Image (cartoon, rainbow, N blue to C red; front, side, top):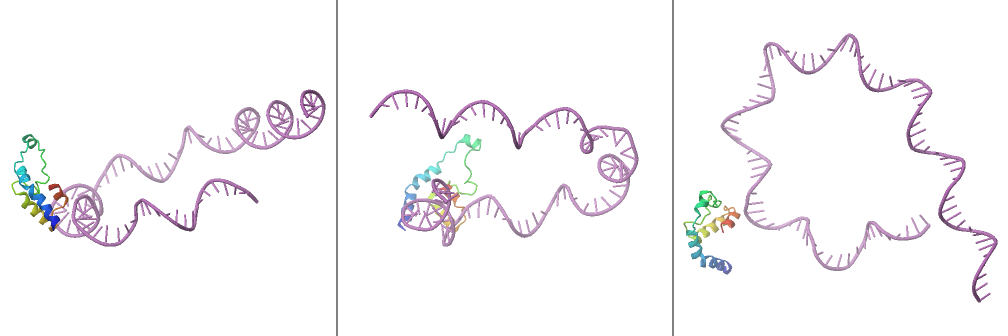
Length: 78
DNA sequence: TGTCCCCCGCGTTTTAACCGCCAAGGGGATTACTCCCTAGTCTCCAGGCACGTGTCAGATATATACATCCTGTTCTAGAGCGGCCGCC
């Protein structure tokens, strides 16, 4: 219990910076013109943009417990 | 018959094997829509098969000729023997 608590504290303490970095992810216009940005996780909805990272990773953990996340993709999302 | 070096029986310490357990994700297995070319004819015709035959390379023949193997004679190296020489 305390180990999972410390892991969630490590998630939440940097969450206010990670969410700000993701929400202000300035994509390169030249990479968008040439189709160079990574859209591997954006097709299945694994992107963290436009939402809080902690609630999204709680939902991701719930579905990974449910066994329909194809776990290595969840590793890539993390 | 010998021998010695190559393999076997066993002590010891690593070393990976098998079961215990967990997901994954290509991949075997199944079902269905569709589509080409293979089953089956019609006709024929040009390549394939039966027959006849001039022929051109293989075999028989034999003196000549290879061709290597077996054997006889000689060359040269090695061990044994005897004569000569120096020392006690």
